[PDB]
Image (tube, rainbow, N blue to C red; front, side, top):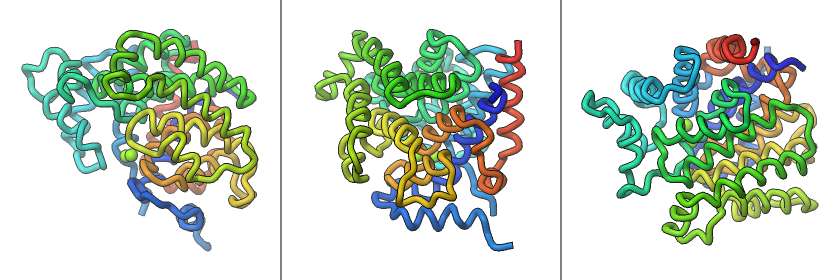
Length: 339
Ligand SMILES: [Mg+2]
Ligand SMILES: [Mg+2]
């Protein structure tokens, strides 16, 4: 498959996960039969699904990259704040709304300040930086630039390293998925390598120690994913216990990656009629918790990996602004990849 199919698939997958997952967000239990009924409703017998903050911020991030043909922190921060101002009720986290209001002050010349000051200067460690970051890996092909600009784009709202390292990890997963066919072993090894390096930086250790986390929350979790994948038939309760299904970036980004890797293979509980991308989204939502955001992240990775051949027409055409998303993906390709 060509890279254009992967770019289109990436942003479609992210849109599908947000749209299809939104109904269940914050539900502590999501029966698989309920999710299957939900997706079956997208293929009725012959309203759109609305997107949430995850897509609104992903679109603003991509708009900024297209406009400036590069990461531009001021342009992107203002676009985030203005998008919230225009359409505030999309399901944003309570934490980021405080940053947006501060960014809307003309006297705010340092666009990193509002995020940095949150939580008594510790910053947010939620997954808002990661939920929107896929476009960075479409604009920047080098693994060094992916890390650099995933970090900076995340720091506009999520200044804790526990937040921005989650955004880096997610961006790296999308970056690797763009490379195509891989064993789960190889995929994980490459990600583990990066996180072991990044979690040794001083800020990383300091933030984790301040949080009592016996540290390396991402590296430890990537190791756990390898162990989970080795198990014959792991329960959702174990997956949630070991990895999480939460708003914290370390309780959602590894989980998304697990769902991607796990769902490469068939699941006897999920009808064989569903392809791997559909399976990934169905399973991720069935973990409950922060379902739109875990699914939007798993969907970005799966869409980059499987490309448009696994993006279901029925689901996609059910999603608010799917044509807009697709033309934005094409435009990222033209601006950043075609040359
Ligand atoms: Mg959302
Ligand atoms: Mg969410």
